[PDB]
Image 1 (tube, rainbow over the protein chains, first blue to last red):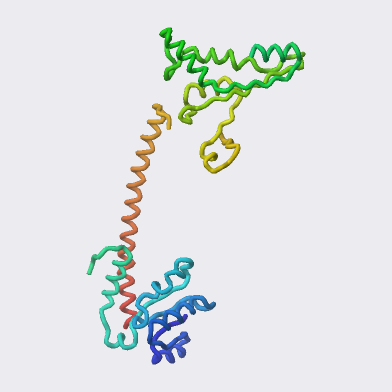
Image 2: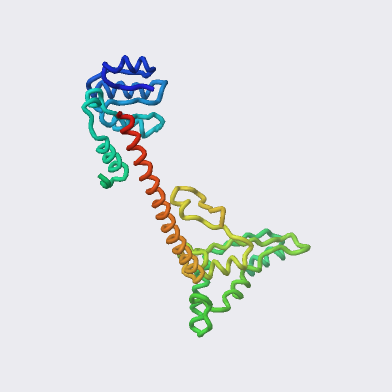
Length: 104
Length: 118
Length: 52
């Protein structure tokens, strides 16, 4: 599987066997992500939230054709150690899926 | 039909008979029946309409020992495209089949618009 | 559609079928709601474990 993240953790990704790339702007993140979508290989791409909060919104026209690629957003290296509540992400997820806001 | 029968069974012709609109014949029959206060059939038509139509259709056929033949192609209009109307019902009870045209096939430019299932 | 008594009976049967189908689909939606709640709880737990 591939993962777009900060350059610091890219060496650790390469050590663990993960395909890591280092980038800091949304433009290159989206272009590289759709390049990973079109290219043959692993179908899973992991995204740091600092570059692209919703990768499905980036590939929404490639997602309408095929739903086999898998995308996963996660906190970046700086956001990881300072931390946050993941339950806000859960509330946003359920509010997106149903269209309804409940169970804070 | 008198002329057709004479030609076919006395002069050995092969006669094809076309009747343009049996609906108008049924309308005239209903006029005469309603003038005489007859007992109606289902909608308006008199109760004896089955027998009267039978004397028209059943004059076709072929006869043993003769070369002639009579074939009939009546044409009639189902009023609201309705197969359960009395005139198509009695016609389908008397005749030997039917060819049913379809309006949906006609709207698509298909000619002839014959619907094969009914 | 030609109005007959048999047609009226068929239409009323269709109406009863439609109402029963609506009720059955509501029950199915209820079951899906329960499964959705369980799955979202599991997903939240997995997300925080992944963060740690």
